[PDB]
Length: 257
Ligand SMILES: N=Nc1ccc(S(N)(=O)=O)cc1
Ligand SMILES: [Zn+2]
Image (cartoon, rainbow, N blue to C red; front, top):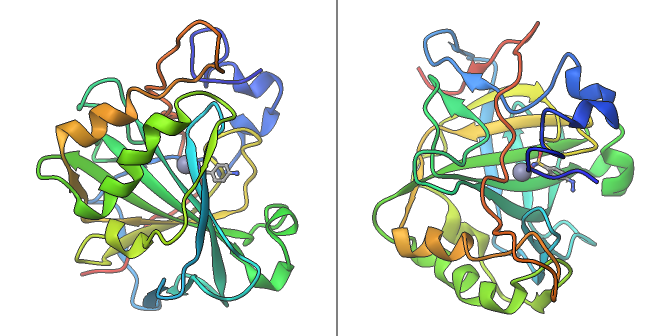
């Protein structure tokens, strides 16, 4: 099945998922000179005060921190969004080296990693129904660069030894995702897709301009995870990013002048 290797990676995905060559695929390169400030964008509201984390899971492609989304507890509103989007999970994409790992790029610059906070539109009742709609999901993307440690990330980093291999999970309650945000909420936005199979074209992307800084030691611990299951030959979980896809008939809008 699909992955990030030579034999099952992004260049192969179109065979099982023909939408891979579609009209609104993600990620994309953000050309900062071509992105236009949009005054019609309303203020972006990240309301994570009552977020209730449950569990962390190695799914063989990345690790997901999962949230209780049975009520409006952690939500994203405003900006390009109509209505309320509920946080369901976050995960990261990262590289084998500090010079690659992000999915989105900014004037062709690749960051060391990218955080995706995944939200679904509550008008569709559940995330499974939402992902079948053009305005079903909103993903908040945050770049990671290597520098100073991110204190709010360390609790994630410390649990990774317990979920080394595919299918392993651990309790992960009382994690505050507000500790992963940068100071500024300036962003770019465009209509796109999931960046992994099934590549469904159901995502409003909101990509923050300001990266967060994480330490070399923090990212090195991401790179000790395994794509493989327990007892199987070790394949380090690195370079789990899809490269930039054609922008086609899309405009990237900026929230800032
Ligand atoms: N669980 N399905 C998915 C959710 C988010 C993404 S991404 N990478 O586009 O944020 C991919 C798949
Ligand atoms: Zn992602």
